Amino acid sequence: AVEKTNSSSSLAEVIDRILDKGIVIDAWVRVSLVGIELLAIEARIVIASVETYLKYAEAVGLTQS
Amino acid sequence: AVEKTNSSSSLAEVIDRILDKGIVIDAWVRVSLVGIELLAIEARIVIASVETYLKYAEAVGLTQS
Amino acid sequence: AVEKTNSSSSLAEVIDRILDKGIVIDAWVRVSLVGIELLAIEARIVIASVETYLKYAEAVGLTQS
Amino acid sequence: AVEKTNSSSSLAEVIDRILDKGIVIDAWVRVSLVGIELLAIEARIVIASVETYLKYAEAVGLTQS
């Protein structure tokens, strides 16, 4: 272990710091007419650590609770 | 760890400071006639930390509460 | 950390100071005839911190209250 | 922090001093005939700090009061 004057390193630390903080993007569009809706699209993309997905699933009920 | 005269660094800190404070943009348009509406569009885009999305979902009821 | 004679910095601080104070623009037009209206358009665009959107939603009733 | 002989600075302070004092422009036209009106247009544009919009909304009743 030798200290470095620069914070540059390999991609392993970049991947770790990307995964630990978690990434999720939600996109949805709703179209309605005269009060009623005729279509509704909704989706999301998730890339995060495995620990938070258990918590997501138990929030939505997949995990035992 | 060596102190630097300039605050410039890699993109990891930029990504972290972007994600922690949270980003959300809401766009919607409503058109009405003689009192009644014939169409209404509404949507939003969210890019933030995973911690605040649990709070959003429990505010809207997805998370267990 | 080295003091600078000029306040110029990167775009991160500009983005932070833009987002913290909040931005919202409201545009609406109403057309009426002989007392009654035949059309009414209203919309707004919001770009602000995530903290104030919970307060907006609870003011309009989306957040639990 | 170094004192300057001139008050010139970046655009951040200009934006802050523009937003804090608040901007609102109201435009409306009313046309009437033999006592009764046949049309009336009214609109306004607002660009100000988020704090005063809560006060506007509670004045018009949107905010809880």
Image (cartoon, coloured by chain):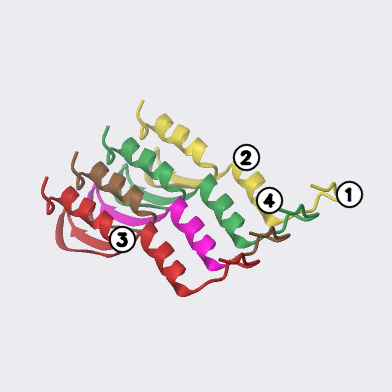
Chain colours: A red, B brown, C green, D yellow
A44 vs B21, left or right, is left
- Indicate the chain on which mark 1 is placed: D
Badge number at residue C52: none
Residue occupying image coordinates x 61% and y 61%: C11
- Mark in front: 4 vs 1: 1
Q: Which residues are magenta?
A: B10-37
Work out whether disc 3 and disc 4 sit on a shared chain. no
Q: Residues within 10 Å of mark 2 (few under 14, many from 20)?
A: few
The number of numbered discs placed on residues in the rendered structure image is 4
Residue beneath disc 4: D14
Q: Is residue B28 covered in magenta?
A: yes
Disc on the earlier residue, 4 or 1? 1
- Indicate the chain on which mark 2 is placed: D
Residue occupying image coordinates x 27% and y 54%: A52
- Look at the numbered disc 2 and give the secondary structure of its residue: helix
Residue placed furthest toward the right? D5
Amino acid type indicated by mark 4: Val
Disc on the earlier residue, 2 or 4? 4
Q: Residues within 10 Å of mark 1 (few under 14, many from 20)?
A: few
Amino acid type indicated by mark 2: Lys
Residue beneath disc 1: D5
